[PDB]
Length: 554
Image 1 (tube, rainbow, N blue to C red):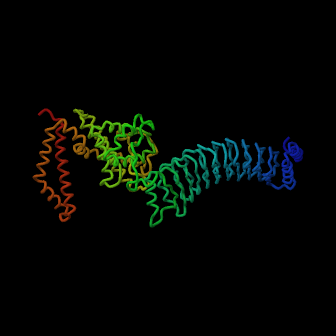
Image 2 (cartoon, helix red, strand yellow; image 1 turned 120 degrees about the vertical axis):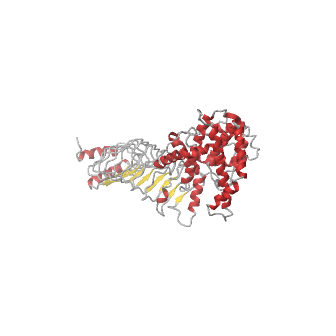
């Protein structure tokens, strides 16, 4: 019994009369009729609360049944294009007609969604329980997925111009087709901004987990507004953006910002915390008791300053949460034996000349440790260990040169997070034990696939001529020398004294003539500095070359 004319008619009457509520059953039956009787292709009968729905006539182009109480839906005409089921609660969605351009189901129940036909140009789903999206016809220019929890946001059509998911639980986004113009996400969890095509007027992300600014944002038109308010951003990133924004000439596309961790952190001297605990957890395992006594201290505040500052980039927890280099170190200061004094005293010069910037400081702590490790006697004549560290430590050294060099091109990135990127990636290439060894894409901005192996090559180079000279001036190396070979160490000064006495002033003169800089009250000083530096390099290379040397038969 495929549909006849009257077949509807009898069945409809049964639908109006059986189970009338106070009114609205039959009123649709008047509507069902006039849409049939006058052949009008579309019908609303949305307002009138109706438990269920009857059969539909074949010639229908649109159906507006919405704002009802309707548990489920009947069979659809193929002929259908516009469908609004919106506000009536719906637990399941029937099979769709090919030619539907417009489609809406909002404020409804179902978790499950079916296959959208090619001709479909529009999809609205506003409040829902669905967590999973099927295939989108490339034809589709509108996606309202907002407000219902979604982890997985599928591919987007070639043709999508609009995307809205608010309140979804999605972790990251797919990259967006060029047509895309307006974008909305709030109350989500979002790694980062996925490249944002230049057509775009407004993307919106208030979803307070995004770590950094893609820096590809400044390619976008003047009245173009995007929103990064309430995201965790480095004091550096925000401050940078702000300075960048208050500008004689135009910011970029107007971007909307936040405030974040209280009151101006990379402007000078705002605050200092105490015994900042990144330690195995908020589990202190006796800590803050132990670092309490130090709280009354001198030089402890300077240290407190670069405890926040170094936290800021890696307190994102990013890469390994805690103990990445974190918890093992401050247990070393816990014993002191001059170590702390050592650590605190270096921490002051972070804010001293070199003025304000970082990353030499973190390097320098590790050096001051070895300086201490070596000194307290940990190298007996075992040089082998001390060989591989210095060689490693040189690599780490050269990389901070590199970060500093890239970080003055990029304004959205702390100097250290650039570095913090290289350390984990090159961890394989260049042997690195001080590598936390793994997190992939937190390797931030800049950091070209190539520039990563443009750096490896670089350090591969300096290692060659420059390293042998490196060890001889290094820290710990001296700390081992004074202990094991005292005489030769001593005779090294005997000789350093000599040059200072003898050729030193002349050595300078010679040097200044060749700079044509003799007048300068300024260059005369870098003259000694170079000579004083050079002969130290000279002296202490002799000193090392001997200490470890192979030539036997005579």
